[PDB]
Image (spheres, rainbow, N blue to C red):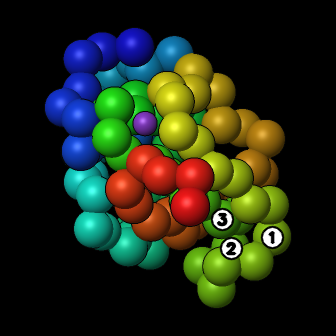
Amino acid sequence: APSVDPTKVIFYQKKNFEGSGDTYAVGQDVSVPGSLNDKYFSVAVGASAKVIAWQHYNETGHYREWTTSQADISDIGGLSRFRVVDDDTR
Ligand SMILES: [Ca+2]
Ligand SMILES: [K+]
């Protein structure tokens, strides 16, 4: 994965971290823009950042927690909403 600052994550519209990336940071709750809905397919995850992610905008459907970089997030079945939070198990 490309280098990413500890408190940040970068979403890509291709698998394997290809193409231009969109950077988000700890403290952001994001409903993905209409034009980018379901279009993110990999994510570089910074050392102190954690992504809480949902298939649907209303925080339902396939659910994921990503604490490490993901080369393929196809399995969430179309990413629509996520939060970037401090990377802590508690
Ligand atoms: Ca979706
Ligand atoms: K992390």
Whole-Å distance between the Cαs marked 1 and 2?
A: 6 Å
Give the residue drawn at x 19%, y 32%. Answer: 5
Q: Is mark 3 within 8 Å of ligand 1?
A: yes
Mark 1 = which residue?
61
How many residues crowd mark 3 within 10 Å: few (<14), some (14–19), many (20+)?
many
Does 30 sit left or right of 55 as displayed? left
Q: Residue furthest left?
A: 5
Residue 81 seen in the figure: yes
Q: Give, as a three-letter code, the residue at label 1.
A: Gly
Q: Is mark 2 within 8 Å of ligand 1?
A: yes
Task: Tell me, yes or no, if residue 14 can be seen here.
Answer: no
Asked whether disc 3 touches disc 1, contact meaning CB atoms under 8 Å apart, the reply is yes
Cβ atoms at labels 2 and 3 below 8 Å apart: yes
Q: How many marks?
A: 3
Relative placement, left or right, of 68 versus 65 is left
The three-letter code of the residue at mark 2 reads His
User: Where is mark 2, residue-wise?
Assistant: 56
Amino acid type of the residue that numbered disc 3 sits on in the rendered structure: Trp
Judged left or right of residue 3, residue 29 is right
- Going 30% across and 68% down the picture, which residue do you hit? 28
Q: How far apart, in angstroms, are the residues tagged by discs 3 and 1?
A: 6 Å
Residue shown at the point (24%, 54%) measured from the top left: 25
Residue visible at 51% across and 16% down? 16
Please rate how many residues cluster around mark 2, counting C-alpha atoms within 10 Å: few if below 14, some from 14 to 19, many from 20.
many
The verdict on label 1 being within 8 Å of ligand 1 is: yes
Residue indicated by mark 3: 54
Front label number (2 vs 3): 3
Q: Position of residue 77 (x, y in %)?
A: 77, 51
- Sequence order check, earlier mark of 3 and 1: 3
